[PDB]
Image (cartoon, grey):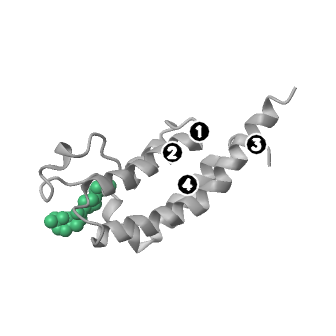
Amino acid sequence: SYDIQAWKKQCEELLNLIFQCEDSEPFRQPVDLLEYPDYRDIIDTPMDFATVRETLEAGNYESPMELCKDVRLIFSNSKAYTPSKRSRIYSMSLRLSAFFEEHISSVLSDYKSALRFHKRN
Ligand SMILES: CC1(C)CO[C@@H](CNC(=O)N2CCN(C(=O)c3cccc(O)c3)CC2)CO1
């Protein structure tokens, strides 16, 4: 497909699948802080899947690369705060990241192909 706009609904559907994954439970809403009062002493830019979905629906992503950067930020934040590899949260982040990356690859490739087609002549 050379549809330049198709990534948005593809990302909406992928976020729906991520919300149905039990493994997204730790990452659905902005970090509390009452449970992690030193979170901002480690994490510069909090990110969660609800914030990514609201940013998409507001029309405040221009490309799927920008959405992908924020989703990758969720997993880097979780790694930056994980006190060890043998943490349930860390194992949840790795599985959900693998699922995300498996599904976002086509969405990025199709978008970049469509833009190249748009500027072909
Ligand atoms: C001592 C405690 C209270 C520690 O917390 C429980 C296990 N969970 C974590 O350690 N997390 C830190 C890592 N996370 C995040 O960076 C994150 C990312 C996006 C949104 C979001 O809301 C958090 C998730 C939660 C177990 O008991």
The secondary element bearing badge 1 is classed as: loop
Which label's residue is closer to the chain start, 1 or 4? 4
Q: CA distance from mark 4 to mark 2?
A: 11 Å
Q: Residues within 10 Å of mark 2 (few under 14, many from 20)?
A: many
| Picture residue at 34% right of the left edge, 60% below the top | 27
Numbered badge on residue 113: 3
Estimate the x, y position of residue 73 in percent, counting from the top left. 40, 48
Q: Amino acid at mark 4?
A: Glu
Estimate the x, y position of residue 9 in percent, counting from the top left. 62, 52
Residue identifier under label 1: 63
Q: CA distance from mark 1 to mark 4?
A: 13 Å
Quadrant of the picture in which ligand 1 is shown: bottom left
Q: How many marks?
A: 4
| Picture residue at 27% right of the left edge, 40% below the top | 44
Which label's residue is closer to the chain start, 1 or 3? 1
Residue identifier under label 2: 67
Q: Residues within 10 Å of mark 3 (few under 14, many from 20)?
A: some
Q: Amino acid at mark 1?
A: Ser
Residue identifier under label 4: 12
| Picture residue at 87% right of the left edge, 26% below the top | 121
Q: CA distance from mark 2 to mark 3?
A: 18 Å
| Picture residue at 53% right of the left edge, 66% below the top | 99
Q: CA distance from mark 2 to mark 1?
A: 7 Å
